[PDB]
Image (cartoon, rainbow, N blue to C red):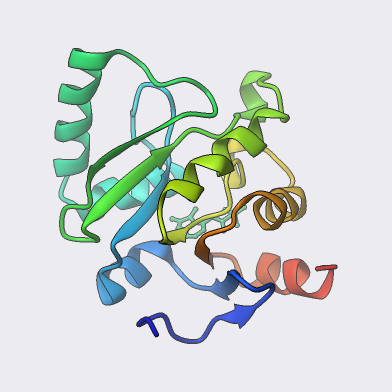
Length: 167
Ligand SMILES: Cc1[nH]c2ncnc(NC(=O)CC(C)(C)C)c2c1C
């Protein structure tokens, strides 16, 4: 038993809800919140911009030190950093950005990072300003993640479409 509330159960381990991941993180304080990151950890907009704003830019400060030491992530890769006031940890995961021309096949590799964590709160990878089809992202999530994932979908209209079309 965990503290997530109001989710629809899609499969044995995948759950979905119309919610703002920022507000959801601030209430649940999950062990792991997933950020929709880029390889430079520049958290300017989309989910990443919103999570960082909620940390009063502390996420960005930590991220800049990480990149200065380690260099950029790989598309499809991840790193674990602090969750600041939102979660114990933040798993920064880089899904392909279609608006940059990146290979959509890398979306499965991106979701594989979730399997290193028993329970996670997450957005749909590569959705939103990353340009991928969210219905496809949900399909890849369900077919790749085996640990317990709680998906927060900000847009109410998109959520209903995701549910109604889920096979
Ligand atoms: C600030 C914020 N918070 C979120 N929490 C969960 N999911 C999110 N993204 C989407 O739902 C996909 C789109 C944007 C509807 C296509 C977001 C965003 C952009």
